[PDB]
Length: 233
Length: 54
Ligand SMILES: O=C(c1cc2c(ccc[n+]2[O-])s1)N1CCN(S(=O)(=O)c2cc3cc(Cl)ccc3[nH]2)CC1
Ligand SMILES: [Ca+2]
Ligand SMILES: [Ca+2]
Image (cartoon, rainbow over all chains, first blue to last red; front, side):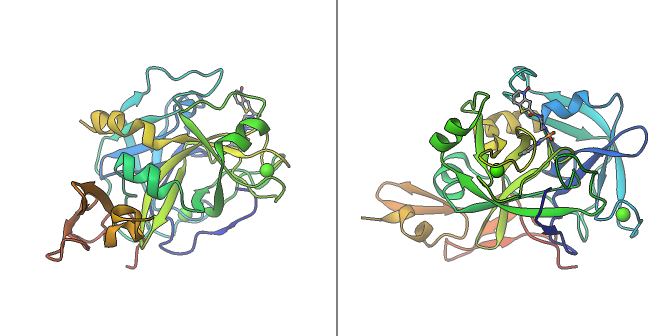
């Protein structure tokens, strides 16, 4: 995340971190239930074996709330295309169930039509992660969050050099220097309604991070709800 | 002119669907619908969608 603020205690509890062999974060995930993590398909090629850490806010210290879980099943979307990042979504089934507790708790899945007419027409959602703090920079050691405005499909297509499919939506700022960035991918984009957070997107891609006239592109979770339901069995 | 689900979410806490010409409310998994048919009551600690308070 470029810009934004730290997630304070208890504020981003649906966040998960995929960590490689070297115990280093390479991508985010969203907690869906005690066994299922939502992530981007493109993260599945950024390492050979990986685990999932939950409950972490500062990867430089063990505040005794963290847990690592091994992955049992990976369900990648069968139409993922690496060239365009279309169908950038995957579910992970964990070996052992998550224990919910402070900083660890799932985000809700919405109903499709209600989410489209009610959630995605709010002004903003929240994206969170441990990725880079600027394009050239290093990964954050603290979990960060950023409020990002939803952007008009039309404006976004005008702004992008790559094709924005119906499986994607854009969020972020034209000029303001605030955006997700590398390492944040696969992480949550959630939308608050009254006092509950629903998962609305997955951090997928951008042309750099926080560039003027570019936005962040997120997988449109609502196009995949049936598929997610299936995968969780 | 805004009616049913389009008027402040049908007074529902979470999902709102217009069945016939009236509002039907419902709740995410891990919530139950209250007797007033509108509010959603968490059935455990750590319901989805809530920042953790302990
Ligand atoms: O410019 C590209 C693209 C290559 C592409 C794109 C679209 C389609 C196809 N290709 O090959 S964007 N890069 C550079 C930037 N990085 S990244 O720093 O990992 C990154 C992920 C991300 C996600 C969001 Cl929501 C916003 C900014 C981001 N930067 C992402 C990759
Ligand atoms: Ca830590
Ligand atoms: Ca921008």
